[PDB]
Image (cartoon, rainbow over all chains, first blue to last red; front, side, top):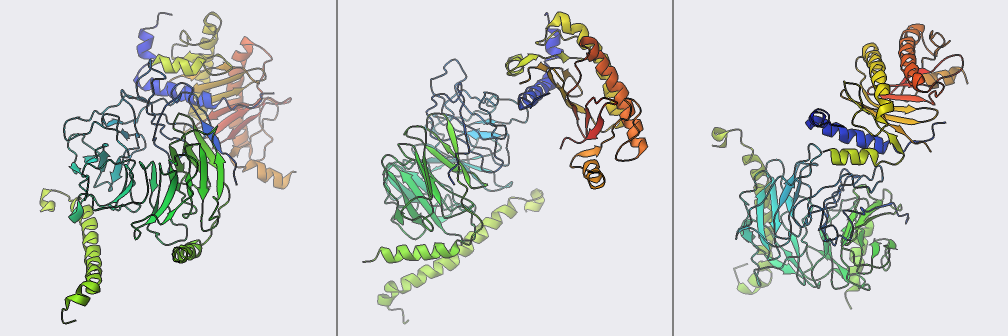
Length: 397
Length: 48
Length: 93
Length: 93
C-alpha cells in the first residue's frame, strides 16, 4: 500500500544487503527436497546479459572458484540496459539467472580482479576508460573514471597487468598502439611507467593479448600483430622492448607462460596460439617456435597450460574444438579433445587452479566448463627432459 | 688469453656473456628485494 | 533497491507468498494475501518473539538467520536475521 | 543398534544434543543426561508448541514434516512424533 516511510524503514541501507541475503538464501533454498576423462563438468549462460555478447576476454577465477567475472564486451543485444556487462556467477549452486549482474557505462573489455582484492574489480574499455568496483556491499556502479588524455589510451585494453605485492601495487594498461601505463592500484591519476614499448622496428607495437611471466618476472612476452613474441622487460637497461622472438603468425589470441610445477623443473617455456591456425611451442632459448603444433582447421584462438600436470595445454579454435595436449604422454594427438556447441570461433580458455577441469569461454556469450579426470601425482620431470631431448634429436637431419 | 680478438670474439664473447649472466643475475636480485624493502620504509626518517 | 529485491523474491519458482514482517508485525509489503496474512503475521510476530526469547535465552550465542519450516503441506523457508523474518510459504514438489 | 549406535547418534557429525522428548512436554529419555534433555527440549518444546498453536490456529493439523530451524550456532529441529515431539539441537555446519 502507501509505503514511502516504509521504503525508508524497510528498504534502508543495511536492509538491502539483508534482502540480498534473503533472496540469495531462499533462491539457494530452492534445492529443497520433499517435505512428506572427458566428462563436461558444467556450463553457464545469461539469457539477458550474456546474450550474443561478442567478447574476447573475461576475468576467470582460478583461485577462489564458483565466482568468476564474465566481463563481457557488451553487444547491442540489450540497448535498454547499462552498456557494460560483468557477471560473476555461482558454480557452487550452478545457476545462470541474472542475480550477480554487474555493469558499467562502456564496453567492458577484460575487467580483471584488482590486486589484493576479490570484490574490487579493475577494467579497461574500448576507449581505455579503466573503471573500478569495490563491491564490499552488493553494489555495481563503476566508482572510478580514468582520465583519457594524450598520455592515456583510447584503444581496447588487451590484458592489464598486476605487478608486485602490497608494497608495489602496479597496473600495466596497454592500448592497441602499445602504450604502457603503470597506474598505481590506489590512485587513478598518475601511471608510473607511462611509456611506449619502443622496439628495434615499429616502436608503435601493435600488441595483441600479451602474457605475464610466472614468478613476478618482468621478462614479458607480448603477443602482437603477426605472432611477434616481443620478449622484454618494463624497466632496467631495456625499459622498452628488447627483442621480438617470432615465427608465429597473426594477432596472438592466446599465449601463456609456464604453468604450476607438478614435479618438473621451472621449465622456462611458453606457447602461442593465433591466426596461423595453430599453437607453437616456445622457451627462453629459441628465437623460433620450439614446436609448432597441428595447424587445425580454423583460427586457433586461446591456449592455456594446466597447473596439475604442468606439461599440458588446452586450445580451442575457429570451429570451437578444445584440444588439450600433453606431448610427454600424447604427442601426435591431444590428451583430450571435445568440441563446443556447433563449430564457432571462440576466444578464451582457462584452466581451473584445482586442475582436472577447465572453464573455456566462447566469444559470443555462454561459457562451457569441461571435465577431464586423468592426471594424478606423477613425476613428469623425467618425461619432460626426455621429450625435450627427442625434439632436440628430431630437428637434426 | 693474451687478448687476441680472434678467440676474443669467437669464444671470449660467450665468456663475456657468461660474465653478463653472473652480473645480470646479481643486479636483478638486488633490484627485486631492494625495491620491496626500501619501498616499505616506516617513516620519512626511516626512509633516510 | 526494491527492483532486484521484489524481483528475486516473488520471481523465485513456486514462491506462493513471502511475509516481510517487521517489528510492527504487519506484512503490508510482501507477496502473501495481505487481508488474510496481516493478522497471521501479527500473531506470528508475537510467537516468533517468544521463539526469539527461547532460542536466544537458553543458548544466547545462537541467532536465527534461516527458518526452513518443512511442514506437511508447505515449504515456509523463512529468511530471517535480527531485523526481519521473511515468512515465505512456497510450493513443495 | 543400541550402544555403538547411541554413541554414533549422540556425538554425530553436527548433533549436539539429541534430546528426545518423552511424553510431549517432559523430556526424560535420551542418549544423554536428564538436565540437558528436560530443560532444553521442554522449554523449546513448550514455546515451539505455542508457535505451532499459532500456525495451528491458522490451519490445525498441518503439522511439521521436520522443522529444521537452522539457528546460527546450532540448529533446532522439531519433528512431531506420536507420544512426543522431536526437539533436537544439531549444528547446521
